[PDB]
Length: 514
Ligand SMILES: *Cc1cc2c(cc1C)nc1c(=O)[nH]c(=O)nc-1n2C[C@H](O)[C@H](O)[C@H](O)COP(=O)(O)OP(=O)(O)OC[C@H]1O[C@@H](n2cnc3c(N)ncnc32)[C@H](O)[C@@H]1O
Image (cartoon, rainbow, N blue to C red; front, side, top):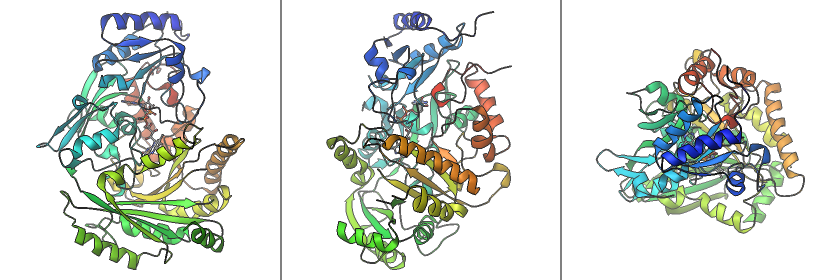
């Protein structure tokens, strides 16, 4: 009987004003709050008028979020509700156009002891979903402990990265952040608060991990901790080609116990990058190579509560500088604290902000591709599409460190069994600075995607963005397993049947049919 027409701001405001009256949660409907909640890292505009929510909700308790989700799901025309972490998304993933954005930071009333509780005996930290990874790090280090898996950039929320995967140079060893969670407190789209883990409501736990915010809002994540090292020996090695870079990265990320190899188990972190556009020396070698150079980045942790000593580090660096195929005379080694290494990108952000180059559009593209096609991709993209800004990252990870039961999508089919253990990530992290940059960079991104589809390179987007369910099903979830899309829909029907959660992800726009 009720109309399917989208609930108006009038109906939404009446429901949420009721919530502001019956809970300690606060509501803002003013243009300043809604303009901020309409944008993300993808744009630098004051407001994205199309993405503007009807209101911003400032929860005091996870129960306020539960009341909001229940109120929307049970109403005549359910309204969109989206959690916002730091809005580091670039394609509107945290927007709730004509709906309600949940300011997750409000739960911390962002660093707060109550939201970052360390259990020394249990070797875990109970972190609020809104908490930043930098604050999780400092809270753990105060007890000589550390999370095992990171993102390169630490000013991201626990709930935000866990809804994607959370990748960095440690993922080859300990898996992404989603592989390093003991339990979660989740507020489902239906408005229930469920504590879940591999032992209880595993279906919700696995759905939420890499789940693009489709099943519920993470209000707490219990993160396991390892003994913390004190320092890190940090290497940056130049390479003249993709072949030796990738071959060496694979040697470094090899599983020491199972596969082995001379360079296995030496590095605690392995990344790489492409430079398309001591400065005069690098520029001279660039012309000789053909305009494109590569970097291998590594780190060996030592000291503190680690088993690796400063003497062990010298021995490992000696092995790596002898065995690696980097360009001789282009090896850069630095010694930093463990915290300085993990928080390294902060110096980059500070520098960019100071030059007015941070608050600019970010037409980013992140991909996962099989090891078998990395050289074909390098030839067509790094030596083609992207041939002359921002960094271009390239590095391998180990599939075995990822749990296939979660929502996360890798470039493998579940039914193909144990194929290639190694896959690559490519991060095209450019900033639109000059006039015409945005249109040019967005077209180059679309061109990378069209080039892969045409060359038959299986390509999976990390932080995916598709407009149709046909693309989500056949291009994204489908090549990952015959039951992946059916599993995603089954979980959606169970946890968010009205499809109100994170509609900015563009998977669902309307309640699921019978
Ligand atoms: C901006 C940026 C992003 C980034 C990065 C560096 C920068 C400068 N480096 C990364 C890295 O090294 N490794 C990696 O895995 N990701 C990296 N990113 C991307 C980043 O992970 C994503 O942008 C991610 O979304 C985390 O950002 P944030 O915490 O800001 O989250 P969001 O953009 O607001 O929301 C993302 C989606 O998740 C939903 N959401 C938000 N909070 C929750 C909670 N608590 N529970 C459930 N869902 C939640 C949003 O609705 C949205 O769909």
